[PDB]
Image (cartoon, rainbow, N blue to C red; front, side, top):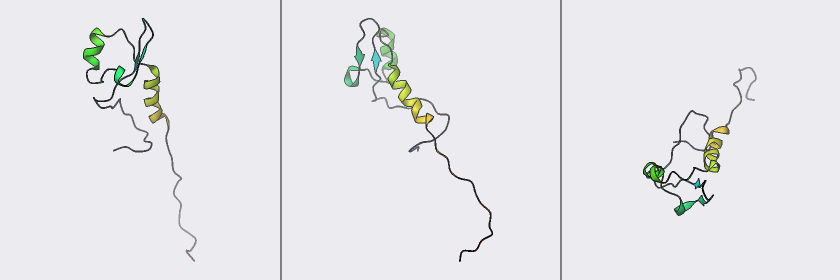
Amino acid sequence: GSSGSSGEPNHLDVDLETRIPVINKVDGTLLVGEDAPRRAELEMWLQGHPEFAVDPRFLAYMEDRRKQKWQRCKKNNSGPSSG
């Protein structure tokens, strides 16, 4: 599993249950929560309901996850005494 922040080349990973927000282009209505379709049925939905468009706010969010990263210090040699 991955926690906190991990700098690795990964792809979009979500759960079928998870919904996908989309902002209509014809009228301009934003879909969120129940209003938005299901990632799983997103394919069959984007077939006849392609009149919408996945909001950018969602995409960006994900990216960020990777954007951030962490780092530690280098090692050292011996010499001094514990005392």
